[PDB]
Length: 166
Ligand SMILES: [Cl-]
Ligand code: NA
Ligand code: NA
Image (cartoon, rainbow, N blue to C red; front, side, top):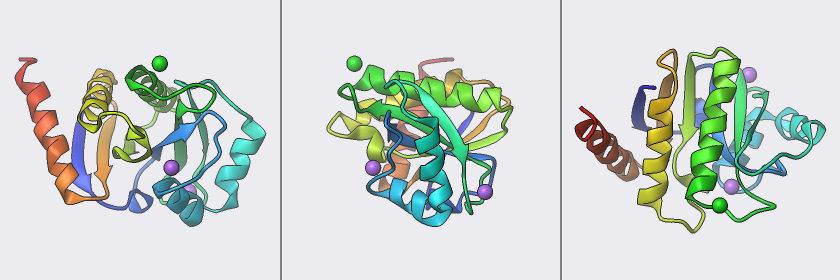
């Protein structure tokens, strides 16, 4: 695709949809995911109840409640099975396919939060980048970080990718 790394509150992201690290149970929990449920409303989590449960590595889509976005894409990285880079690579790949299917234009990823979870951050970020760059250019993606520092670190990675890809 085409990604832009920034520091912000994804619940403030104006666009079509936001993407968040999830557990295949689709049960919204800690950190920013909670902000989502907080800003969005009971609609989000309840949509998940109805949807049911999925497979780690896959993603599911719900409304965004009050959020400025139309949808919330839930990439499953842990749950019935332990999380891992391939669990991230896959989950991330599905999240994108979801948006494509929905024919979306703008989508933001929560950055490295519930995406790491014990794994090497520098690694997660990279496998996550690569997948995003494989996504259709009809997609304008934004990597939103809580902290400006990580925002640069992503920019540093994003640059390393563009370098060895001529
Ligand atoms: Cl695995
Ligand atoms: Na979380
Ligand atoms: Na909304």
